[PDB]
Length: 454
Ligand SMILES: c1ccc(CCNc2nc3ccccc3[nH]2)cc1
Ligand SMILES: [Zn+2]
Ligand SMILES: [Zn+2]
Ligand SMILES: [Zn+2]
Image (tube, rainbow, N blue to C red):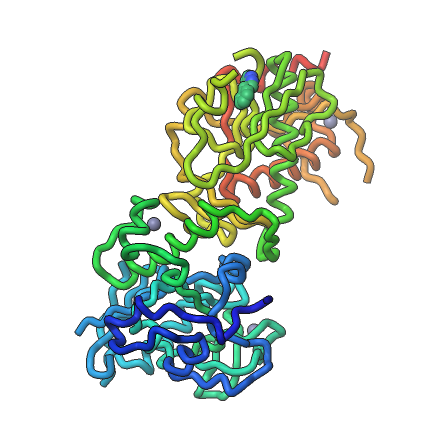
């Protein structure tokens, strides 16, 4: 069982208000047929338009919530809503658009999906809370067939053009009018009691229902992210490299060794309490300090309460490297992912949180500035006790107050420490822009690092 069988049953109870008289016994095969699609027994990599929950999770970057609300359905205008905030009105003749015919509506859909998805995924997955009109309206902007490649590259085809009779990926679909071979999943098939608004509002207060299709589309994908990444966490699932994943991770590791090594040299703590990831290693293996580990997995719902992390039976320093707590103690070094960051790695989440996808998927709770009241923002600095010796990438004399080296203390930064400073500043910028934020105990002062050059 790799894919979802077309002969699997589809519960049609959620469809019988828009589609009265719908058979209670229904398969995906009859549903697809009812929707106006002829699969014609094709063994060509597209076995079903609908997918399993496991396949949807593997493709979370492709998720677009989709809802259709019949404003007045053959004779009536439909309101098409997407989890991008877009509301299009199709006439059968926050971004709310006026009534236009399907031939122009379909052009806008291809443009919107391509601009939203070209840097996230090789496909689209329409996340539904299916009542009927979204499924029946699919024939107006979707064409299906065998799996294909783009006419301008080796990526899989996600669009089709009736104007040129050609196929394209999200990057080369400019002017294409049809969504080709999309995927979809109905959240209403997961066994929920009650309507979408009531199930969604149990876990989220950020999304409301201003009574437009996009509001329901946003609530749909949000409820789907909750079930698959907040209440359920599968950390075995690997995700493709779509950006600066490798650089961002290596940058985070360089920043961590730097920041922790310097705090231990500056304030000479006898013990460091490392709270977080159970698979953690000492980031400064040669430090004098008594290193003590505490296991706490990445919380994906609410930020850990310091009362429960600690008090259950102030000396030294606490290291909270990506361990999201409600209020950090004053003696801490903290790396905290900012869920508000706009990037191709950070997808929107549930209750203000976000889905950060870099190798694994991590739903992170909403960033809260009040978690850091006992700390201050960590300033940039580069520290090095390594010998001044080149080994060699051209040079322009470096002058900086934040290059804490013997050469800068002695009056002139050497070429080696200037290359190492410029590389460290790039890794630092990479990490800050990726969404991470650095915080430290208020007594941290880089002025104390100069006296380690005796
Ligand atoms: C079950 C059993 C015991 C515990 C507390 C362990 N002792 C501890 N954790 C610390 C963190 C930071 C600083 C000092 C600490 N001492 C928690 C859960
Ligand atoms: Zn292409
Ligand atoms: Zn929500
Ligand atoms: Zn030097």
